[PDB]
Image (cartoon, rainbow over all chains, first blue to last red; front, top):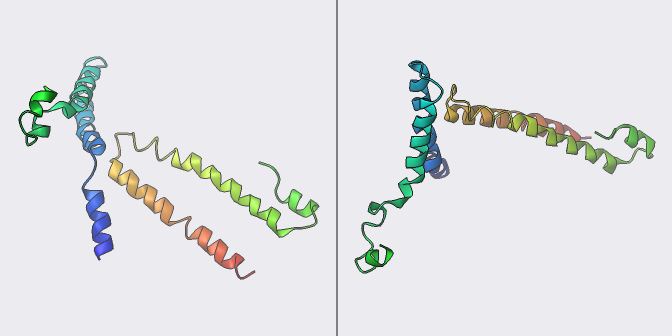
Length: 74
Length: 74
């Protein structure tokens, strides 16, 4: 039961590349439910890909690294 | 794609030339590529294609284990 629980707890705790994948499949379900075009849907997918790739630049990522170290990074 | 049962019956019927039939299990690339062209298909949930991939790994590891279990009796 401990082995099954550890395997299930590392599969349930997914990575960010599948949180982005199911963030961007119901988005495709919306863009194909309401029949969007072929240019602005590229803008939507490009914007969510760009904000996912730029999500690893936050100051809140290092909101506990002390001052005069965050100041050196800045 | 070499004929490994004409080579077997030509080379004095040696047992260790019939172990080269197991090279033909590299043709499961075409099935694992099918489950990679299906995981990026947004019509089916990716956590369901992972379950179908595990259920195609569960069987064919009981087919191969049945064949090896009979071979170890022969």
